[PDB]
Length: 91
Length: 88
Length: 91
Image 1 (cartoon, rainbow over the protein chains, first blue to last red):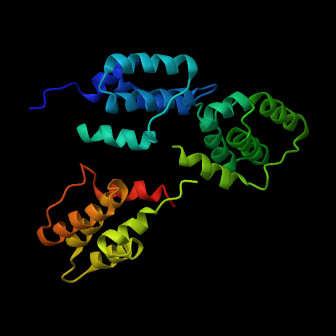
Image 2: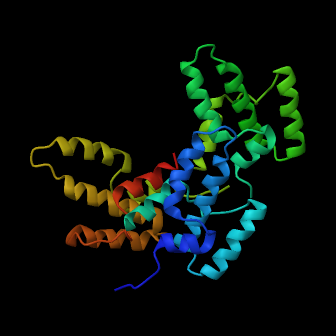
């Protein structure tokens, strides 16, 4: 009954990009020339973290956008592996 | 703050994650340029983890790129790579 | 500086059993006979959960104690896999 937003939906709301397209991206960023996997990985890492753990999307958007200029972030000690595997319980 | 892999790109102008895929595909090799690759990572990673002044890191790394001489306070690649991996 | 009890220490204070010897137990119980792998896995699961998340040893001890008579427990959605990984990040 928990009628709610999916964690993919929040990710898009927050970051403006589709979560399901991202791992495909991270893959094709890894086979590359002058790729930027670093920025893609941290993008997905922080967006996901926010989609999973920040209930306030309004703030989460603003906070993400900050990181887009500063490139600084924190995810409570949660890496991608860990965050992604959390998100996968919904799939 | 800035992730250590951000610092690595800032210091070395190359993407840390790419650079180990590079190391694998040089291990199989023809004229394995694996030594330059290993030490490029080893030193950049070391600076990225332990030198908080980027202005100095860049130029220390830069010097290394012309001289191939470097130091990482006895810390080999493997140690450094393992430290970095904690944040992953 | 973070002068604290390790989670393996907490695990012993809580369950009376040595965390390290426990996964060796889980291997060898797995091969079996009348292998009591289920109770072993839940012992570690809940024990590790309490070690990583309950600060109050007195209350963890007794929460676990009740688990030993009822086998009822909760680790907040966290399976063993997930719980052991968390702990492995402190080795």
